[PDB]
Image 1 (cartoon, one colour):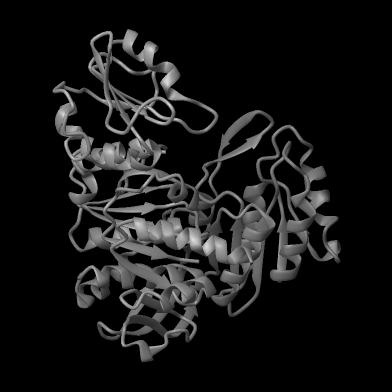
Image 2: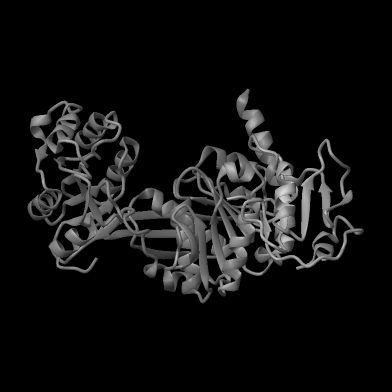
Length: 478
C-alpha cells in the first residue's frame, strides 16, 4: 500500500509513501497510517490534522472545500497532505482501491427495501453456498462468513468486504439501507446484482434514479408485486421481474419469474413457479407469503447470475429460516409451532397473518410484553392477538422489575373480550399450555423472543429459550 499508487487514478503528482491502515478517526490513527479528513455530520476532520500528524501518520487526504484545489499536494511536518474535492462522494472509491477492490474479487449481491432484506440476504448466502460458494453476509445481524456472523462509513464497508475476501469468501450478500446509499457508503462497490424487495414522489424518485445511475448495480432483480417495483421495471428492460401475484407482464419479453401456485401447509410452502429459465417446484421450509416472495427474489437473482436451475432446485429444501424468524417446529402428529421475534403490534399482526396461511385448525398466539419499557404497545398487541388469532395466551416476556401481572393487565385492557383470552404466568408454562392443548391441525405462534435465550426476571438473565421449550415439548431438537 503506497500513497502514490493509491492516488494514481486521480492525482498523478502524489508522493511515494508506504501506508499501514486507512482511518477517518484521528484518535486511533497510528504510525504509518493514512488519515482521511472529511467534512460531514457536524464535524470537520481537518481540525484533527495536527493531532494525526503528532501520532505519526504517514499521509493525509483532506476535503479541499474552502481550503485548497482538487489534487493540491501540501506538506506539513514532513507529512504529505493531499486535498480532494467531494471527498465524501469519493471515499468509497478511495477505500476500494486501498483495499484492493474486494467487490471485484467476490460476487457481491446488494439487497434494498423496507422488509425482507435480512431474510433475502441470508437465503442468497445459504443457496450460493449450497452450490459451492464460500458465502458471507453483511447486514443487520452483523458481518461474516455464513455461520460466523460477528454482530459504518464507506471505509468500514470496504475494509469489512476485504476481511471477508481474506477469509476466502467468494460470495457476499449485503443488506443496503436507503441511508447507506444516500451517504455514499457503497458508492464504488461493484454489485453483481441488486435486489429490490419492497409532488413529493417525483423528487424522491428523481433523487433515487440519479443515485442508481451513479452505482454499479449489475443485474437488477425487482419485486413486481410492489407498486414502486413496477415503476422501476417499466424503465429497466434488462431487469428481472419477480411476482407471486400476477404482476409479470410477459409482453416485455424480458426476464421474469412467477409463482403460479403456492400451497401453505403445516411445515412450509410448496411453490410452483414458471420463469424464463424454465419451470419447477420448490419445497420451502419458510413460513408466510412474504417469505415466498423473498425466496423467489433469491432464486431469480441466482438464476440471473447463471447458477443452473436444476442445481438451485436440488438445494432449495436445505434453505433454512433465520433463527427465530417465523421458525417452524413440527413433529409427527403434533400442532405446528412457529417461534418469531415479533414484539410490536405491526410485527405481531404480520406474524399471525403469515401463520394463519399454514393453519387448517385454530391459530394460538402466546406472547407478553417487556417490563420497565414503554407501555403504549401493550393494549395494541392485545387487540392484535385478539383479532388475528383464535386463542390469545397472554404470558410474561422479560418482566424485569415491573409487576408481571400489571403488564398482562395493560395487554388485556386493549381487548374487546379480555375474558376470552387465556392468561398464564410463567412463560414456559404458557407455551406448554398452548402446545399441549392445541390440536394436530392447529398452529401455535410463540412471539416476542425469537432467537433470544434468556428471560429477564428482576435484574437476572435466567436461561430460557422459546426454541428449546418448544423443541422439547415436540420431542425434536432445536
